[PDB]
Amino acid sequence: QVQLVESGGGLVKPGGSLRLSCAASGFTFSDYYMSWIRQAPGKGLEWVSYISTGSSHTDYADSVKGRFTISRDNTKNSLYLQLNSLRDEDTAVYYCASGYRFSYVSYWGQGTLVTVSS
Amino acid sequence: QVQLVESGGGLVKPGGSLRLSCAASGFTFSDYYMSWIRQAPGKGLEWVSYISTGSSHTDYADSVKGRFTISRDNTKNSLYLQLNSLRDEDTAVYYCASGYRFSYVSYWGQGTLVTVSS
Amino acid sequence: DSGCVVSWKNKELKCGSGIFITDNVHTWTEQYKFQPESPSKLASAIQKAHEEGICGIRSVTRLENLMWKQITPELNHILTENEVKLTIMTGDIKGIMQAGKRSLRPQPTELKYSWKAWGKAKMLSTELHNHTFLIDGPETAECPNTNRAWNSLEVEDYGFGVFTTNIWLKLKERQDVFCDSKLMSAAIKDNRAVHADMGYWIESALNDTWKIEKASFIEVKSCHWPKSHTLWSNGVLESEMIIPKNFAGPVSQHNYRPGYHTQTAGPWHLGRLEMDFDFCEGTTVVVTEDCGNRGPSLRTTTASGKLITEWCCRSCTLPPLRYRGEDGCWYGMEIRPLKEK
Amino acid sequence: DSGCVVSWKNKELKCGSGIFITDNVHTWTEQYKFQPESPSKLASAIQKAHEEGICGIRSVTRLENLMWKQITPELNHILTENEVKLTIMTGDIKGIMQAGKRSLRPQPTELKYSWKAWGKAKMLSTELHNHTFLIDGPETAECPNTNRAWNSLEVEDYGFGVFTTNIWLKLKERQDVFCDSKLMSAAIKDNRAVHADMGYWIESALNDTWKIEKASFIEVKSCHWPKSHTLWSNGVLESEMIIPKNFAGPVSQHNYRPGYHTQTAGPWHLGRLEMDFDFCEGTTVVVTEDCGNRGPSLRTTTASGKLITEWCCRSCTLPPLRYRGEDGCWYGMEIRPLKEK
Amino acid sequence: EIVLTQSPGTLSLSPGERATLSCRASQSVSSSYLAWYQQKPGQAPRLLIYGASTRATGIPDRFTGSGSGTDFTLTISRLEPEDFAVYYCQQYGSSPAWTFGQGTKVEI
Amino acid sequence: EIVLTQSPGTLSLSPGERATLSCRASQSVSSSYLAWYQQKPGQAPRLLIYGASTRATGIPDRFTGSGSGTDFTLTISRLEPEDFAVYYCQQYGSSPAWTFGQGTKVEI
């Protein structure tokens, strides 16, 4: 069964940094596109970023250009996102989802929560 | 009749300068090419330079590049050559000839004599 | 036209006179800013054509839209000042950059109730009339391209300003299909032949025989490439250029590639493309005669995002032809899945 | 390929990537120096061809004559070291640069009695035999170009040195008539189109219709200009070329000019030419229908140096076509004296 | 941009009825590339239609996806007390926006 | 360079004879472009042949120019005591050298 496990969420000071990891199992991780999706509290879902299989496309959202970094490790089936220069509105539940902006999303798992305040 | 009279010849110290003039009459001076021909004492004839009708060709001999300057004035039928940086082998009789290197020479007149020594 | 050029590949300095072909397609293409000729001629050209029965305007180039996107405040002022029951609304546009069937024309007798400057201020909002005039956009239903104008403008001969944030434009005196020759170039120096404009960077190179090597597009226009700027444009068959003639492909023998024919059904619907000859990541291409015939280009990722590994080609030539866009890596017509349907 | 170039005509600066075209035809054309490939191959290439029945070599480019003028001391030594009864003498050159009928070929199996370096010392003079092998020169009587080889060499791909005083050359593997494409250029940017090589600077411009404007030659070769470096090379008639095809005239529509046909019998015998469109000094051309038909080009000065003032043309187009050389000012084919014989 | 619109913002019904949805599209979706996701508060989203017409694996039969062109309707044939959640519609190509749908609240 | 050669270096004759001269050419002059000049000692040179065959104006008929190809001969039909001078041959195109001929002295 496709299990997606994530960790790294927590309260951080504005302007800090964080790293989010995704643990994939139950399916061919090195064969599907990978993406991160966030959801502000009580608001709609919004794309964040996605990465290709060989890590060569790596497209990012408009409001996080240069602030976020996404990477994957197919050998151990791990997906990584790097948080840098966090601002106030970044507080959202971040979902590690098996998808691509030009495709539907098949697998979602227990997205973590991150807060940026004092 | 075509008389070609020249003046300016005289003894000069090496490294000096001199100016020679040609006076044409009896024919359309503003219609032919003009050229200066020098002849070392007892040696053969040799070209020096020739100028076009509108003063746009003004080709010079190989051994006088940058040292000799030629000019003409079609208004009063005169032909001018300017001597600069004279050396000891320039001692020759200089003929004002109505001709051109790619043509025969029709009129010659009373070539002047210039000597470069001490 | 005279200067010194440093070359990183040759590690040498080139000094002399001649012609330098600027890239102006990568690294913040600058600038080709926007201002047309006198406003009265353009303003008078709308309602005169609207009386004929025109309904919209299409932009031949991507940047020509940005002419309209910032000028529509101005024409709305003058037409209202001329009590004209019309409105101008521009929008976004996407490939394929469609082309209309007719074009504007003078009537050089312009409006007599206009100013002269093109930088007037104090814009006043206008009303909307029952007669609406559209610009290029997703309006392919209410009015077709038959009642739509296209290729009605031309770059002014004195309109070339690279540091001055402006480029003068004037309307053509006749209908035409070719692209703007005034801002257009092509060159070749002993190893590479490049055809270029504001949107295209078609580059060809010689390894054993002259052939196309790479191309980059920020737009996919529909004007035919003029032959006055085509290198080796004789004896070229229309069924063999890699870039189709309809998409401003240069009619030349440098647009050739052995084993591949015209890509009339490539993924040109993407706004940006990058043509090269390599392998898409994680994919392999094997030459075999039992592979399927050429069809529409296929994205290397399915609707679920899964990657298709193995591919076959009938009579292709490695490295395979592939495209870089916003969708991933698309293969050419002659490449088909080895076993996937 | 990336740099910043100032433009005097536009008073502007051009910075970016792309291809820059060196002049290499005015202002001390530099350098195209000459060091060929291994001398053992070229030395062995002579006697095997001499046994076939060759008698001499002609040159295709004016500089190539200089390579022979400084290589025959090496060639004479190596063949004499192989007790080959042969000798080599080079000569001067003048237009028109004639062309032979056959060429050299490997035989890549070279002589085994030679050194390796190209800069050896202690050169020893050789003797003279009854078998003499000629090179380009005023020898059009004893041995014609039929028994003379031509266009046997080719510019090495890696033998391109613009700063290092060497251009490596190897002999071709097949018969050919086209010129050397390894050192050749052609470009066009929105106002001008220049076809250029080591000797030609054919330049065309656009005022109302694209047409030739000026050309400069330091040589007059006889190899056909390749079509891979020709701009707008489709539908071009060979009877309207300004420069004849036999004189390396590029096959293009940019080689056109209204009112003028091919200049088959122009003043090409001169080594250097500067073709433009103006009036010879002190001359006037008047368009009239009763003027004589086109013939060979006539110098503006007679055999006595007298200037011919008035001229007429039948269906020419002002300004008239005129040539600048070392002989004066020659007019075109379609220009005839008004009343003089 | 083909940013979509969901109407109505919220829906009120009772178990035993038959509900319908509506995901307005800006213009001319390509190849009917639309999807539906269920957001049971509060858990991870699920997948219903690929696809705009085809039921996804592990999904009960009552979930029916339909619509074509520029109008799409997600209809549940049979109501069920656990089915009350938030549903989102997404277009994938081309070219999709950077955000999902606004969502429709289903309330008793 | 089509530098010419004049032979012989000097000529010895007597009045009433018939003299001959020779101006050797390097190779194949074009359209017989050659001229002859007389240098009376000591005066400015005159002009005799245009031309290599055409007598100049005011020249006595005894001066006959001939030759074609690469060999040219200037022959005076009748000797005359004033005719003893130095004669130069020039080629005018193409391409001519930067100096005239060597000249041949005619001595009694």
Image (cartoon, coloured by chain):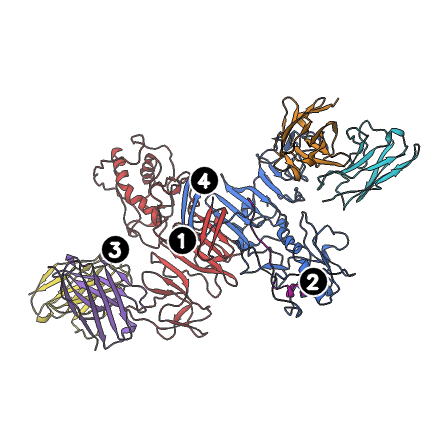
Chain colours: A purple, B orange, C red, D blue, E yellow, F cyan
Tell me the element at label 2. helix
Whole-percent x, y for residue D306 in the image: 69, 30
Q: Mark 4 = which residue?
A: D8
**Magenta span of residues:** D27-43
Image quadrant holding the C terminus of chain E, namely bottom left
Q: Which residue is mark 2?
A: D77
Q: Vertically, is C208 above or below B73? A: below
Name the residue rendered at 89%, 29% in the picture.
F81
- Disc 3 marks which residue? E1
Residue type at mark 2: give it: His
Pinpoint residue D256: horizontal percent, then vertical percent.
Answer: 56, 44
What's the distance in space between the residues labelled 4 and 2, CA to CA?
53 Å
- Distance between the alpha carbons at the discs numbered 2 and 1: 56 Å
**Badge nearest the viewer, 2 or 1:** 2
Q: Depth-wise, is mark 4 or mark 2 nearer the camera?
A: 2
**Amino acid found under the numbered disc labelled 4:** Trp
Which residue is painted at 77% across and 61% down in the image? Answer: D131
> Does any portion of residue D7 appear in the rendered image?
yes
Determine the image quadrant of residue C70: top left
To which residue does mark 1 refer?
C200
Q: Measure how far apart labels 3 and 2 are at the Cα level.
A: 79 Å
Q: As drawn, is D299 to the left or to the right of A57?
A: right
- Residue C82, magenta (yes or no): no
Q: CA distance from mark 3 to mark 4?
A: 45 Å
Indicate which label's residue lies in the foreground, 3 or 1: 1
Q: CA distance from mark 4 to mark 1?
A: 27 Å
Between residue C324 and residue D159, name the one nearer to us: D159
